[PDB]
Length: 564
Ligand SMILES: [Co+2]
Image 1 (cartoon, rainbow, N blue to C red):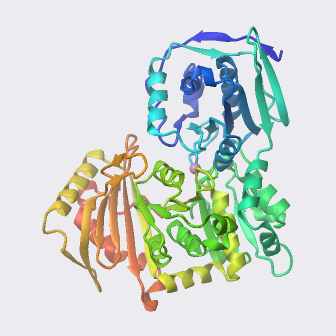
Image 2 (cartoon, helix red, strand yellow):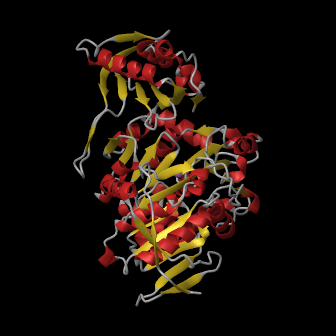
Image 3 (cartoon, protein in one colour):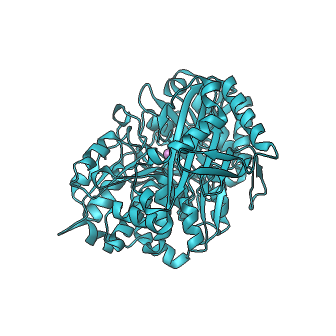
C-alpha cells in the first residue's frame, strides 16, 4: 500500500448540495444511502482551488466527533490526494473543534479547511451530519465561493479518488502517500487535537492568574460541561491538566459519537444536567458548550443564568482583564441586530464603536478583517473575538475566568453590579416552531405595513404601569462597510423611546416548518426594577408585541414552543 492509484469515477450530480453559511447538513442516512453524495461534494469543494495552486495548498480537516466523521475524513483524504492537494493537516482521531480549525488555518497560512460538524444538531446513526468549508483567513467561505461549490455540485460528471488510500487518524506525525505516476507526494500531518488551540489561548489569557484562581485554597469551583462533544478534550487538557482545575470540573468531556443521545446544544433545558449540578450551590461557575465548540452558556452559583446578551456586555465592560486586548486595544464592539442592547450601553460608556449587524458571521469577519472589531456577541449563545474568524466557546469561558479572577466577586454579584452601573436590558427570545407558513408571512407583512404608516412613529403603547412610545419602526437593512453588500429585510424592529425594543423575524430555513422568533428587550435602570424576575418585567412588552403583530390571530399559537 502507501503507494496508491488515482482513479476517475463517473458520477451523477444531485441538485440539493447547497453549502449555506454554516455548512451542508443532511440526515446521516442521506450521506450513507445516497451514492456518491459526499464524494461529489468533496470533489466540488476541491475544484474551487485552482489546479496550479493545489500542490502548495494545505487543507485543515477535523470535526466534532459525531457518527460518520472518520469515514468522511478518509473520503476527504482519498479525494484530496487524487486531485493533487499537496497536504492535509488533520486533528488526531479527526477531532478538531471549530475554533481550533480557525486557529490552525490562520497559523499555518492554510488555504482553508473542511470541518465535519453539524454544530448543535443531534448526531449518531440516526442523527444529522454536516460539512463546513473555511477559507484562508480561517473563516466561513463567503457567498461568492459557496455559490461556485453549489454550481459545481449540480453538474459534476466525474471525480478523482485514491480508493486504496487509508489514513491512520490515531497516531501523530507525517504520513506520506506516493501516487502512481504522480511525481510529488501527498502528505497528511496528524496533529494533537488541542495543542495549537491551547497555545493560542496561552498567549491570549494570563494562565498563571488562572492557575492561581482554579487551584488551591479558596479556589473557584467550576463545572464545565462539554455536552459529550468536541470541546471535552480541550477542557481536560487546558482547564484541568494545565490550569489545575480538579478533574471533576470536566463534565461529559469524553466526545461521544451520538453526544450521549442528546442535543449538544447549550441552554437551560438541553444542558439540564449542568444546571442541576450548579443548583446545589457548591460551585462558583458553570458552563456548557455546543457540539463543535463555538457556542457557550455561562452559569453562576446556584444556577444563576447569564444570558448571552448580558455576557458579551460583561466581557466588554471588563475587557482589559484579558491580556490580548491590553496589547491590541479594543477596535470595536458588535452584535447581531436581535441581540439585546446591553453591549451598547457599554460601547457608549467606553466610547467605542458599536456595530449592529444582521444575523450571521460574515458581517463580524468583515469588520474584524478591517481591524474595526475586537469583541462580538449573538443572543444565541455566541461570543467571539478577532483572535480567529469563528466564534469560540471555550475562549469565552476563559475570558469570564479572567474577569472573575480580576474582579474577585461572584458571577451573580458581577451581573448585579453591571446592571447597577449600566442598567439592565431584560431580554428573552420566544420561538414559535413549525407554524403554518401562510399565516406567519401575512403576520410579518401586515406588521411591516402597520409600522410603515407615517403616523406609526409616535404611537403610544400602554403596559399596566408604563407607556412605551414608538421611536422608530422599520424592516432592518445593513450596508456592509467592507464588501459593500446591502442586506435587506433582516427583521421588524419596534424601537421605543425608553431604550426598549421588540423585534420580529421569520426564520430562514423555514422549509420543514416556519419559525417565528420574537425578541423582547426591556430596559430598566431603577434599582427597584433591576432585580425582579425577567419574565415578569418583560410581560408588558410581550403583551404589546403579540397585540400589535396579532401573532395569536395569524397562527393559532397561544404560547411559543421554546422560550430562552
Ligand atoms: Co456551533
